[PDB]
Amino acid sequence: MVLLESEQFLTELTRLFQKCRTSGSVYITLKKYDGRTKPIEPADNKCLLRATDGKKKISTVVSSKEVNKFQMAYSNLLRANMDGLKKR
RNA sequence: GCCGGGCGCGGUGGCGCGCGCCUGUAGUCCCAGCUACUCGGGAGGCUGAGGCAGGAGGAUCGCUUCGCUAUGCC
Image (cartoon, rainbow, N blue to C red; front, side, top):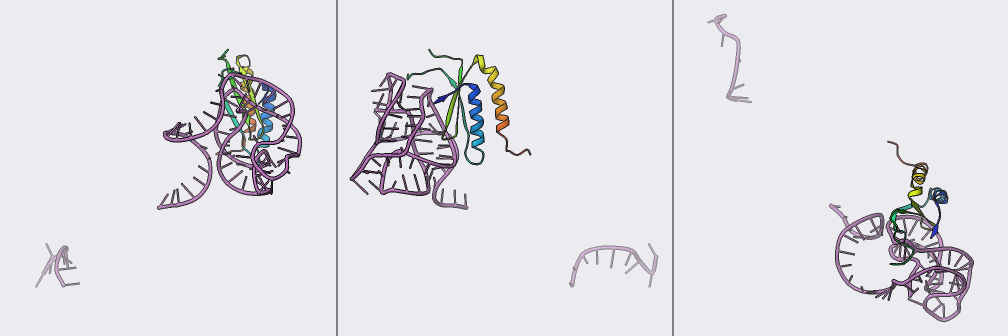
């Protein structure tokens, strides 16, 4: 798939959230990433996040050296783009 | 040989396909065409892949529920 870095991944996730506003759903999947590139070397410090809407899909890999920078930005992006609920 | 799958709607005689919904792998991009006919063509990555039968777990399709008694010639 379209594998991008965190900087472009967040921007494209923003576009997905905006495009799935009036019609469409946003699918976000998080899973521990081993690092394999060939069918069954195995790394234990990677995580994989895939964002799709049915038509366009993007994927990203976050490691230890970038977890600290990516966590806050991802949480802020979710807070900004996941509005539209009841406030009780 | 493999590189998503399924549900409903729609088009086509048919394939490819468009829309909405749900759900995966470490593992896809582009161009719209093939012309009575079961995946049209191009460019990339992989060695294991395909089919059958059971089991638990998601969104959905079809069914549903007249007696008692009280103050008293104090």
